Structures are given as structure tokens and as C-alpha cells.
Image 1: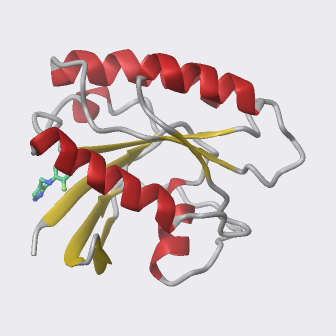
Image 2: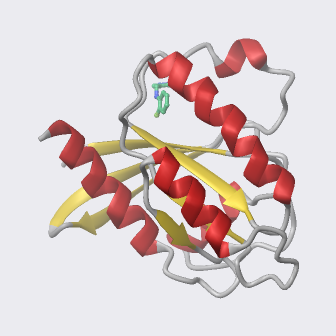
Amino acid sequence: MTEYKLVVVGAVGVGKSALTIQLIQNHFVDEYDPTIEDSYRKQVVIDGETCLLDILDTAGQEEYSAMRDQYMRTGEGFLCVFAINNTKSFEDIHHYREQIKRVKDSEDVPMVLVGNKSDLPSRTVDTKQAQDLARSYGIPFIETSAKTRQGVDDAFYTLVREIRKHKE
Ligand SMILES: Cc1n[nH]cc1CNc1ccccc1F
């Protein structure tokens, strides 16, 4: 059994841990929590084989700059989630894009453009925009909702294959 190290990053108000809770025990959290660093591991059957889903959470505080670029010496799976409820988060993705690209020292890397809060009527980011950026980033776009559980597992199963594609 291999442990798939996946790191979820993004802006504040996207609800990163919300997707995790939805994927672990199948539940949508309403209350927001300022998570600094939480550990989430679960054995799931991916591609037929039992794999260990290692999900590490990150803080939304831009004050820990010396922590963001500290142990990020290694990285197998990156998760860039954005919310269509806020256009700033969509633009903030560009900052993380170059940030990670610079730290990774590479361009090609298994990634997925996932959008949360897609069921919210506060659509500030249209679908065309996401597809446009996805084409430039070179990664697929997957609309996901934690409130209605809109294909959550499908957004993970894809990334796992991408990693295996990059490796073999
Ligand atoms: C911290 C730490 N304590 N024990 C091992 C590690 C490294 N793990 C890890 C590092 C970066 C992204 C994702 C990860 F799971």
C-alpha cells in the first residue's frame, strides 16, 4: 500500500477541510475553523488497489511565510482549490501558481483545477473563465460542491492517476 501525499492549498473562505470532512465521513461542515495544520489519513480503494490517502491541511495565514517555503522541499500531489463565490480566490490562484512553480523548479506536475461552492448562487466566476485558465495551466477542471457532494471522489481519483502518469 502506497501513501499518496496530497497537500491542499488555497485562500481563506474556500473551505479546504470542508471537502475533507465530506470525503471522510460524508458530511458538510457549516462552521469555519482556522486550521493551522491537521492530519487526515484514510485507506481507500483507488484504481482497484487499496491506497493510503494522506491529506495535509495548511493555514490561511500569510504571516507564516517562513513556514510555507520551509518543508516544501518535496511534493508529490498538490491540490489547488478555488471558490467561485469569490473572484479574488480565482485571481489568487495565479499567485500560488508561480509560487509553487518557482519552489518546485519545474513546470509539468500532476495538478487539478477544482472549484468549490459551485452550488452557491453567488457565482462571481463563470465556467468559461475556469476552462480558459485550465487550458493555459495544462490541467483539467472539475466542478465540486461540498454542500451537495457534487462528484467529490471523482476529483481525487483523477489526481491520483495523474501522479501515476507523471511517474510511469
Ligand atoms: C511534516 C512531516 N512530519 N512528518 C513527515 C512530514 C513530511 N510530510 C509531508 C510534507 C509535506 C507535504 C505533505 C506531507 F505529508
